Picture 1 (tube, rainbow, N blue to C red):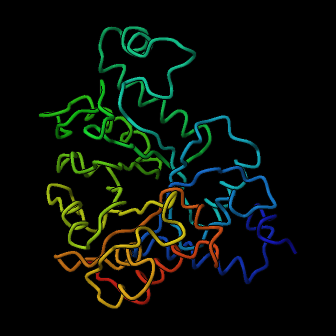
Picture 2 (spheres, rainbow, N blue to C red; picture 1 turned 180 degrees about the horizontal axis):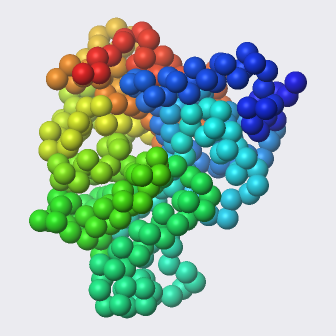
Length: 326
């Protein structure tokens, strides 16, 4: 007889709640509008539900951890264990990929020094192979469910890995064996690889190694301006693997921007029409977007109800306007 925020394993629940989360775990594996976000201030520290993966809406499928790197608390480890095993949930490491050494470069040592000669052996590429293997290390160490490449060259995050060009042996071969090394390792482990910002630079073939294409559709003011952004037939199965996200650091109150126009007239009489359009987005093929998410998803918690917009959006995407998945 333990309330949820206190529960740690299937052993702490009644039969009726064991069975409840069994259907949630089933659902996760059916094809549906996935729910995602960038979860900040993740502590698992108690009293406040907002700091817990396990207290997220049951309709959230996976999440990227904005800010967290390593050194997890026992209370973080336990939140995650429940989120993973009871809820069918998945948590990703996440951070901008710009330079070869990024966020795994110790001290103030030199990136190109530490990674290339010191870790490769002059072979720049053995160092990309190495830098990636370290990401996987650090994921396997905290049993997280994979990685989220924040890829934004040509929004200023261009470096000794990130550049303007298609990722393929024929274009950015360095970014190619990067992604190749993450897939080789964390795909057979049941883990996820994912790319946000400019997943459109993936080659057709390389796109097969990435489980979702995640776009920041923050300031798009029209359905068809969002479709233009994500309509990339170069990408394997782009409709069902594409996730479109709204900006909740600023629009948590309103369900993104206040001056959006949906292709569904009935959505435009209603506040939050950006996130609801996204969740119900029928692409020109007729297929339903693969999912929606919010940046700083937790800013939706102070709402009435808490997680107002995300919950509504997934209700719109999965029940009000049932989508087509083939």
